[PDB]
Image 1 (cartoon, rainbow, N blue to C red):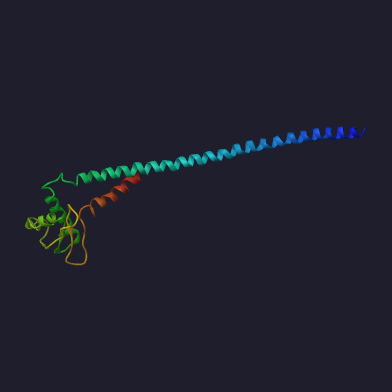
Image 2: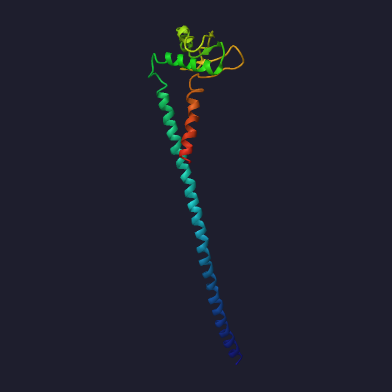
Amino acid sequence: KIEYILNEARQQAEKIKEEARRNAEAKAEWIIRRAKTQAELEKQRIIANARLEVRRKRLAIQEEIISSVLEEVKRRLETMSEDEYFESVKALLKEAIKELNEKKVRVMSNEKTLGLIASRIEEIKSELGDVSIELGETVDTMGGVIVETEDGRIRIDNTFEARMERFEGEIRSTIAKVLFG
């Protein structure tokens, strides 16, 4: 009847529903595989993230080597040398006046370090050529002679300032052409 039309037309629907069912998956299929390669792109970035972590560690493990070694010459800067500091002060002065090249100087230090200078001035002036030295600072940093000319310029062997602080960088250049490469 007119029912017969409906039956055959809904039967068509059945077979229509099919291809579109069939196709509709062959769709999600491809993407499944496409996301496959997509996620392999991800991995690479995972290996990049790992490389970036390689650094975080390296430098941390690098700064550690300096920090302990600074504190090591800090411990070796500390009171382990007694009367060898006077003949270190002596030495430093001989090393400082030399580069500066002047008859006039003034070595500031810690009060007494700056006052211990007033001792063997003739054994100090004896080391290298003769010169003149007068006055110094007291409330200054400790363990080192801070040479100051009676002219414009002044070189610092004061404390760590140009000593251990200089070494910080000295070591750094070494430790980086090695660690970093």
